[PDB]
Amino acid sequence: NYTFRCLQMSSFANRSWSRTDSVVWLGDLQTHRWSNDSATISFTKPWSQGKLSNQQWEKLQHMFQVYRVSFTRDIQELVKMMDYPIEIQLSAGCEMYPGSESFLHVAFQGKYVVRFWGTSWQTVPGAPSWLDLPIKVLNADQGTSATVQMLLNDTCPLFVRGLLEAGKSDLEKQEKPVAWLSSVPSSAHRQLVCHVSGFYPKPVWVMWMRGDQEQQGTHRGDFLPNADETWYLQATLDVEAGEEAGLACRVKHSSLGGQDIILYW
Amino acid sequence: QKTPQIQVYSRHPPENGKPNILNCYVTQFHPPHIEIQMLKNGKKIPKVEMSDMSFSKDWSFYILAHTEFTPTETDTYACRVKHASMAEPKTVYWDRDM
Ligand SMILES: *[C@@H]1O[C@H](CO)[C@@H](O[C@@H]2O[C@H](CO)[C@@H](O)[C@H](O)[C@H]2NC(C)=O)[C@H](O)[C@H]1NC(C)=O
Ligand SMILES: CCCCCCCCCCCCCCCC(=O)O
Ligand SMILES: *[C@@H]1O[C@H](CO)[C@@H](O)[C@H](O)[C@H]1NC(C)=O
């Protein structure tokens, strides 16, 4: 039911310029940010420490502080031996289940190249071959391999468990959708648009209706985020001139207590 | 290099004269370096807040820009994006018909 993702973004412009920024997400709720120009990790929730003690948190952040400086030095040295600008991304974390699976994926120039897998680093089908040498040498780093394994196997699920308890009231908030209608011309024929905004959590039901008859032609757009941690979504329907009369947008959402929004065109 | 997609939408039902919030959601780009301006009548809006840069399963970056605005019968609102994948800044105008 929940994915916890740490997202690292590292840019290397030249020998003397680089930066690293990361963000952390529990479902669709940012819980941390770590700006390059920050010594420390910032909480973007009241509960972003989870159930960890201050001491456990400090220790864990130190570990990340060492890794941040280390990682920068390692890539910079690696390029100096074995083509700019360099973009590296890391996506690590774990997927929780009702009673978890952890991951560490690495991309390079926006191409997924390396993963942690069990006890070691692997280059991924069709990664650059020169990557095998530095990855083998890195697999010789027992200390790193041990820390990574603990982070993924133990630290992540345990920490996320605490988050889930700690952020109960944010994770389970209900914010009601608001809906409105518009339509749009075509090259030919109109398109009905149902705007649905401000709902939380993400799952939602939105359909153009004619009475109780679903207009299966209803096309749901992408979920677009609002800036207050609610979601925006359009559901649209092509119609012929004349056809609009009698149509309605119906929205169902857990926040509504079974009182669906119905808006008749 | 991946080309930015820009979607501009309002937080609340747009109603002429009523303070609202305009969202500019830029997705699908790479590398992460980008410049985003929100515009009113082609002029730079000053107090634009932005989310932290993040990325998707496909590794491509996204960010949310947003600003306070008031829809009217005479003002144009726009989101302009400068990115290395395009020779020219791309502008998408908010259209409430959407
Ligand atoms: C972390 O979990 C991984 C599995 O994700 C463990 O690696 C496996 O360990 C078993 C049991 O010893 C081996 O038989 C497998 O060959 C390993 N799997 C892979 C994919 O290599 C790892 O040992 C765990 N580490 C810690 C520190 O708990
Ligand atoms: C490393 C893989 C799983 C991570 C488990 C970490 C447990 C707590 C996460 C707190 C957020 C730390 C963010 C650091 C990410 C980074 O800067 O690369
Ligand atoms: C990122 O952080 C380190 C230390 O804060 C600094 O030396 C480096 O120049 C920073 N990168 C940028 C782009 O400022």
Image (cartoon, coloured by chain):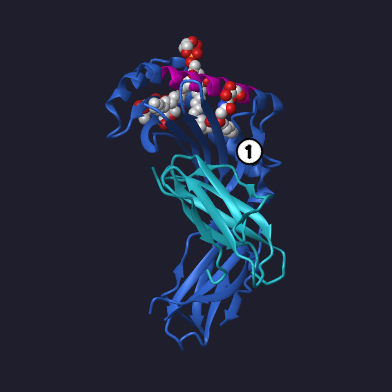
Pick the front one: A28 or A228 = A228
Residue drawn at the location 62% of the way across and 25% of the way down? A61
Residue A64 inside the magenta-drawn segment: yes
Foreground residue among B92 and A207: B92
Judge whether residue A142 can be spotted in this image. yes
Q: Position of residue B3 (x, y in %)?
A: 41, 49
Q: Is residue B71 left or right of residue A152?
A: right
Quadrant location, the C terminus of chain A: bottom right
- Magenta span dominant secondary structure: helix
Q: Is residue A213 left or right of residue B48?
A: left
Task: Give residue A183's position: percent from left, percent from top.
Answer: 51, 76
The magenta region covers A59-78
Q: What amino acid is at disc 1? A: Gly
- Using the rendered view, name the quadrant where residue A162 is placed: top right
**Looking at the image, which residue is at 40% across and 17% down?**
A80
Q: Residue visible at 45% across and 73% down?
A: A218
Q: Secondary structure at mark 1?
A: helix
Q: Position of residue A248 (x, y in %)?
A: 54, 80
Please state which of residues A170 and A225 is positioned toward the viewer in this rendering.
A225
Instruction: Determine if the C-beta at disc 1 is less than 8 A from ligand 2.
Output: no
**Relative horizontal placement of residue A211, taking residue B43 as reference (left or right):** left
- Name the residue carrying label 1: A162
Q: Which chain is blue?
A: A
Say which quarter of the image contains residue B21: bottom right
Chain for mark 1? A
Q: Colour of chain B?
A: cyan
Percent position (x, y) of residue B12?
65, 65
